[PDB]
Structures are given as C-alpha cells and as structure tokens.
Image (spheres, coloured by chain):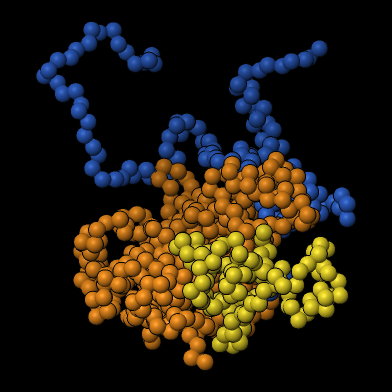
Amino acid sequence: TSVIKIAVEPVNPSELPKMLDGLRKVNKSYPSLTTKVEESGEHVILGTGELYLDCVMHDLRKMYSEIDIKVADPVVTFCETVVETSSLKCFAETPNKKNKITMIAEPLEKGLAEDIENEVVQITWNRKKLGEFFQTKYDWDLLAARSIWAFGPDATGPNILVDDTLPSEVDKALLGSVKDSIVQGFQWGTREGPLCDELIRNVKFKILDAVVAQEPLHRGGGQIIPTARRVVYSAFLMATPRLMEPYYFVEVQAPADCVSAVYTVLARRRGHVTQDAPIPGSPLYTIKAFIPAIDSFGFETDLRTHTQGQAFSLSVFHHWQIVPGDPLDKSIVIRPLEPQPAPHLAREFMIKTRRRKGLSEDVSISKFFDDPM
Amino acid sequence: TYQRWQFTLPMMSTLYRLANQLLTDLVDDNYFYLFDLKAFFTSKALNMAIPGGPKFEPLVRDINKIIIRQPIRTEYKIAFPYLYNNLPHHVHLTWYHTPNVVFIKTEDPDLPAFYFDPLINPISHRHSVKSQEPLPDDDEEFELPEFVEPFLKD
Amino acid sequence: IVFDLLNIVPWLKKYGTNPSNGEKLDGRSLIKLNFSKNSEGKYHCPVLFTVFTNNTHIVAVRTTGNVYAYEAVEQLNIKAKNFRDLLTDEPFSRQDIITLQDPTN
C-alpha cells in the first residue's frame, strides 16, 4: 500500500505542464505509482519505497520529461482514529433547523478493520450473514448487528456507520430515504478527516438521534450529506483523536559480529526486533524487526554502512501504529527545525501536515459544534 | 612474443598463494556501495563528500512544516541521490546489491572439501505433515532389464 | 477571480474595463455573495464548517451566491445528482458555478 510520499516542484514553474505530463507518463508506466495534486497546488507522488522513488525521479527528469525537478524531503501518510468514545452526543441541525442528527464515535473491534482490508467480510453479504460473522467471530450484539449501515470510507474500509435510533427507526418508511444521504455524508467525511486531513482509521459512528423533516422537497439531498459529514466530524472531534503512522518490517542478513550494530541502528530509528536467529543451513543471521517510516529513510544505506556492507535489509509495508503524541494539545511547543522528543510526535505531525497540505491553523473539538448564535 | 598465456590450475592456486598478501578477499560489490564510480561522480557533480572518500571542487559553484525524527543525511543523498537531493546534476544510479556471498576458507587439509563447516548452522528441516503422492505401489508390475549404473560410479 | 464591488466600483465606472481582464466589462453581472461567519468568526464553509486558509479551493454557485468548500460542492453535487444550493433549496445549473481559488487548476 502506498505510504511513502514525495513532494516535487520544477525550478521553472512555467514548464509545469511538461513536468505534469511526465508524472502522467510514470503513473502509467509504474503500476503502483499514484499522483496527487495537493491542496496548495503542489505535485506529490505516492509510492512505496526509496529505490522505487529514485527510479521514478530518474525516469521523470530524464526519459518522460526534460525538466529540472526539485524534490523536497519526504514524509508518510497518516490516518486518523479514536480509541475513546464521545462523552457527549455530537449533533448537527440542518440549515432549516428542522432535521438534526446526533452521532457518537468509538473505536472498532481491533481486528475488524484488518479483516475488512483482507476482504473476509464485506457489506455485500445480507444482513443475516453479516450478523452471522459479526456475532459468531466477535460476540457482537444483536441490535447493532441488525443496524450496521455501511463501511467507510471505501467498500473495504476500516470504519462503520451503525444505527441505534430504534425508536426513530420505526419511521423507517422515511428514515430509509435519508439513510443513503447520511451515509453519503458519512463516507465523504470518514474519507477527508477533521484533525489533519488524513483518513479516519478503525472508527464507528453510532446514530443516537435522527430527526427528519417529512417534506422531501424541503429536506433535499444537498443538506443531509453535509450535516451527516458534520456529525461524523463532531463525533470524531469530541472523541480524543489519535494519529497512526506505518510500522514497516525489516528482515536482515548479518554476520555474528553485526546483529548488535543492527540493534543500535534500529533502536536509533525507533525500531524493535521480533526475531534474531541463525539462518538454518547458512553461516549468516536473520533479523526481523519493525521500524517507523519517517526514520526509515536512509535506514538500509546507513545500516550497510555501519557494518561495512555486511548487514543487508529489506523493508516492506506491515501495518499502522500510534505515534506517542496528542494532536490537539495547544500546550505543546515545537521548535521549527529541531526534531521532536517522543512525547509530542502526533502534535508536530498534525500541525506540520495541515500546514504542508495548505489548510488552516487551528482545529477545535468544537469546530463543527453547531452555532446557537 | 610471450603473448597470450595459458596455465594449469595447480599453478593458478600456487600463484594465488604467493600473491595472497597483495590480493583483496572481496567476492561481491557490497563493499563499494557508496564508494564506487557512480556514487563518487555523483558526489563530484553535487559537491558532496563521503567519510572515507575523495573530495573535489564544484563543477559549477518552509521552516514550519518539516517532519523530523532522524536526519536526512549526506550518504543518504548519495545512496538515493534523486529524492533527498534537490536539483541533481550528473547524478548516478546507486543501490547495486550483490548477494552477500557465503565463503568459507580452507585451513587444514584433512577436512574433505565438501564437509559441513562449524560456522554453518544446523539445517533442521521442520514443518507440518510431509504429504502424499499417488506413488507407484508395487505388486501391480514393474522391473528393469539391467545395464544401469549411476552417471558417475567409477 | 473574485473582488469587491465597493472596491472595483470607481475603477469600473471611470474605465469601462477592469483589472482582471483588459477586455470591457459590464458592472451588473458582478453578483452579490455572502460568506459564513463561524464560531471564532472565521470564513468557514456553510455546509462543511471547514476553515478556509490561503490555499484551500473555493467553490460557489453564482446562481446561489453562497461560498462553500469545493469538497462540499463535489461530494454533495457529484455523488448525489443534486446541483442545487447547499444551504438553500435553490436548484441551479452547474454552469453557473464559479471558483474563487484553486492552486492546482
């Protein structure tokens, strides 16, 4: 999965159509390469590795374009999540103050998102077989098994919308027609994300209230998508939201006198070693470990440099994991170019990421909290 | 003319022995990953320097949003010289990865040439049940008319 | 590429053209717009509530006069077939839509 990122800009901003054409050529030629045109108008490319990206830059700058194409220094895409449910009901009342949705947020069951991703569960199933898997494998409760609505953001995605307005579910001959509208808001929001414009990760929004207006022309469709997005975001924001970065895996072949140098290399890059063994049938050693990604730049370079070509590593995507930080902590100070001591990684991540994409300065847990003004 | 030599392999091993002190013991190109022609001409044109490497002239001559855990280094700008390196000129393609070669030296003669050296690790072929095949059970029929011997027996 | 009428008023009244284009202009088609005031007072999307900065894309139905995020405009207007106003009932022709800023365009 595309987690590694590059920010590109030509020295000549006027040749920019040409560099764009080149990024189109490489998006066609390298099958795992993704291109994004970010919120400040920058060119970004989503890939999966460093030699990968270097092939990309060689080919763009030389064989698919002829441009002097500056590169910034890379970063990885994060995801937004909640480990705590909203202490209060987070609501959005439609512009015509006649409809209103109240939702809550909470973390999913830990393996449910990974099962979704592996494609063992799908909304495609009927309600009964969906509940079958849910209850039989996760001891799920009957009411929410009957009322699981859709999956966010994408078809096989880590988030869910659940119904729990069973007294106002009795209006289902009306609640159904706005079911699709509220899930349009749900998926749109659970894709965008309020904290730092990164995907909501393994979260579930429960409808605690849905008050409808029985005039279809009044209620429309263009207000129930945004209000549903807004209750998604208000629930996500009244939950204390947490960032997630990848944890790449690394398998190393190293001789007798080099595994501890590898230990220092990893524990320098915030890694931990799951496996340290001799390679059966070989005089070499195998080292399996896990590493954070923004430290994973130059990992293999410096790693083979440390034991002089003897160490050798491969790295790939494994999973995402919480960085030790809190994003909406305005009592966190960051010096603009020194690195961050570990207590405050997610704060720097969120603020630097919103600034780099081009968004505003501050986010509030009551930003989407509707106006009684 | 003394042109165009050819030898025998025992003489080859003897010359190897006599020159053993002026001969590197390198089998792979994993020593000069960052130390080779490509990365050193990269360094020349980029005006970059590597710890144990040569130096040269130059061929020519926002703060908020940066995410920092460990530093984007110079040898990194040499090993991936396109990414962490803004504006590359005459920049070569690093990361040539030769398989880390297993080589075990002969020390004392007895030691048949192909014998499990102490440094190599026990095999321990281990997994779940082996498997079945519809193997050709006997009592149905088979038998060979006999000339056969292994391809090298003498 | 937006401005204020009370600002470009004397320029357009004394010169028949404007600063956005050299070609001649009629003042009438310059249509009123109102941008939301939010909890702090910031210009935030009416339907999406997201805060506007120097960079984010700016979208509007010139028929509706409202100014809301292109995110709102699309994910409400493209997924659903509604080209209507986001805060009002006004169904509009999508050709009337204008954008005040898109750094990537």
Instruction: Tell which chain the image draws in orange.
Output: A
Q: Position of residue A72 (x, y in %)?
A: 69, 61
Q: Is residue A181 above or below residue A115?
A: below
Closer-to-camera residue (A337/A267): A337
Residue A222 visible somewhere in the drawing? yes
- At 69% from the left edge and 42% from the top edge, which residue is drawn? A64
Say whether residue A150 is left or right of residue A3. Answer: left
In the rendered image, the residue lying farthest to the left is: B139
Closer-to-camera residue (A292/A165): A165
Q: Position of residue C46 (x, y in %)?
A: 54, 78
Shown colour of chain C = yellow
Image quadrant where one finds the C terminus of chain B: top left
Q: Position of residue A88 (x, y in %)?
A: 38, 87
Q: Quadrant of residue A38?
A: bottom right
Closer-to-camera residue (A265/A75): A75
Residue A321 visible somewhere in the drawing? no
Looking at the rendered structure, the number of numbered marks drawn on it comes to 0
- At 57% from the left edge and 85% from the top edge, which residue is drawn? C38
Q: Quadrant of residue A174?
A: bottom left
Q: Is residue A143 above or below residue B130?
A: below
Instruction: Tell which chain the image draws in blue.
Output: B
- At 57% from the left edge and 55% from the top edge, which residue is drawn? A46
Closer-to-camera residue (A178/B137): A178
- At 60% from the left edge and 22% from the top edge, which residue is drawn? B10
